Amino acid sequence: PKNMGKTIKVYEYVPLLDDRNINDQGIDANGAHIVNGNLYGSSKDIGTIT
Amino acid sequence: ELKVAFNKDTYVATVLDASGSVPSGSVNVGTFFHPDETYPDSYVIYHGVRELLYKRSEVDPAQPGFWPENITNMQAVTIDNKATARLVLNTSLPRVVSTIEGGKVTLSVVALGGKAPLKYKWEFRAPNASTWTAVSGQTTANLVLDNIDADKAGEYKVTVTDAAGTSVDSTALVAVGAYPP
Image 1: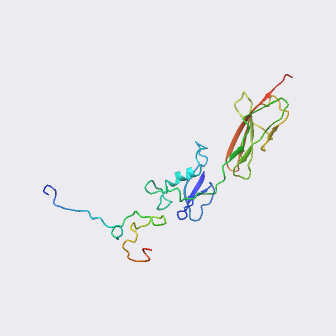
Image 2: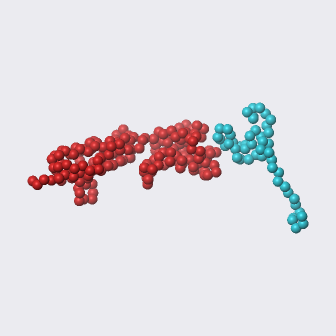
């Protein structure tokens, strides 16, 4: 639309379990704050998700 | 001044005394008066640990913190007390005793606190005065007044002091009818 700058931008909502959604809100299954907020952030591993 | 420690792994809040040694793993989180200075018979040790972990941090229970990130889940912590039990008076002196001149009035106090040398004290206020006068000699619990005269009337106050600093007192007013000589 006119009178509305010269730029269009949208919002992309990323899934929880990917790697792109790194944040600081993380408490593991024991109760200790961890660096990664996403549980098994698309590791596709066995040991990591275990 | 009860000193509290806290290990973040086992979630054990060891309430040590002022001269304790923090356990390997725990870290100093603060200090509080277990016999609260202002309201002495309203809060318990739990009511002092909660006020100490609210100002702490889940990330590391060593740095201070507040509401969004603090140790407020008061179900995982297990208070492990190693502080001497408060000096309490199990049996205090009677409010009033009243005999006649010549009778035998005995007063007894039982204390259950924490110390090896539980020393005692005794004072005496005449019923017109303002300052307490030291009762010389009697320094061991039961105080016996035999052949009590009229001049030995007023208010007696024991003072059970433990080893370091704690003291608890209790009074007992004594009356003696004096028949004419």
